[PDB]
Amino acid sequence: DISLRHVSVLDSTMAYRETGRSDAPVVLFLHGNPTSSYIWRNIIPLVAPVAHCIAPDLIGFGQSGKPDIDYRFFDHVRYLDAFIDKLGIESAYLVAQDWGTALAFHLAARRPDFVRGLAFMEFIRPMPTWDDFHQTPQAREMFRKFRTPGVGEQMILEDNVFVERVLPGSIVRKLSEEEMAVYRAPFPTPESRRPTLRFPRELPIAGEPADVYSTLESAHAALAASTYPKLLFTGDPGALVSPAFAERFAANLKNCRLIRLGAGLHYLQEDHPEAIGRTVAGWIAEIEAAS
Ligand SMILES: [Cl-]
Ligand SMILES: [Cl-]
């Protein structure tokens, strides 16, 4: 059974999904834009036998509160940090996708000993040019429009394009009507959609925004030097991560195994939950037995 809980955090509240035996290591699942802990619903039960699974809804997403903030990357850093402290988590495996990987990389860079292992996919990295972002002309044009004043507000705040187009368009299988009802539930109003507009405007592309760009460059330098166990999952063709890029990226990290899932785009949990869950569970069991 998965439980949906709430925990007071800073000036607001955060929801999180929880399951697993509490005497096992913690695994923290970190979603990105514009999902929530719901995207881990078919993975968490498969890791539950070996770990204490904790999957928060980032502030402003899912069933978490909606404080009056900018929802910058650095805001998410503060709320996630506060969430981890409030639950008393002193060390954890991290499982992450999209902006959840930026949060995971930055957490690991600040507290390297916190990470028991990092399983990541479809991750954010500093992108020196627009040619380094994604793979398709239509994605490049759309995210350029997100980052254009006025245009981005119309597409995302008024028309909810990140939830209604980018999310189902970046998954191979068809989402059910109920699944899309869940994913749009946090975002019924223009004002509620602010976090899904701020995130693409935070993506580190061509040096902007400079603070995120610098921060993720440092995070990736720490990642490259780190020696904790790592799993990089990839889809084909993928989206932010192509198979060929994943192969080189993992081969240039220390202690990183590459898992090729097959047909996938950006939100790989919706196309390969059992492969991801079973692989993570076996990887944790391996690492825990090795102690
Ligand atoms: Cl996600
Ligand atoms: Cl984004």
Image (spheres, rainbow, N blue to C red):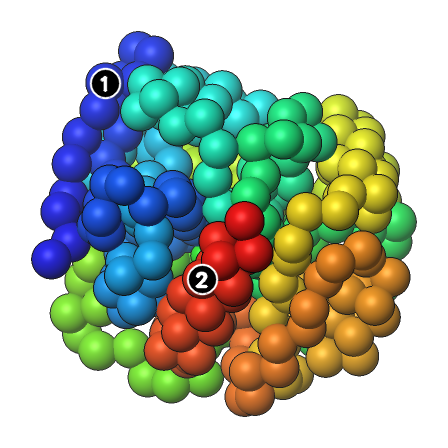
The answer to whether one can see residue 32 in this image is no
Above or below: residue 39 compared with residue 149: below
**Badge 2 element:** helix
Residue at position x 45%, y 69% in the image = 282
Q: Quadrant of residue 203?
A: top right
Q: Which quadrant of the figure has residue 61? A: top left
Foreground of the two, 131 or 50: 50
Residue 163 visible to the viewer: yes
| Foreground pick, 62 / 108 | 108
Q: Residue furthest top?
A: 11
Q: Which mark is residue 8?
A: 1
Is residue 29 rendered to the left or right of residue 78? left
Residue at 62%, 82% in the rendered image:
260
Question: Across the whole image, how many numbered discs are drawn on residues?
Answer: 2
Amino acid type for the residue under numbered disc 2: Ala
Q: Measured along the vertical axis of the image, is residue 31 above or below residue 153?
A: below
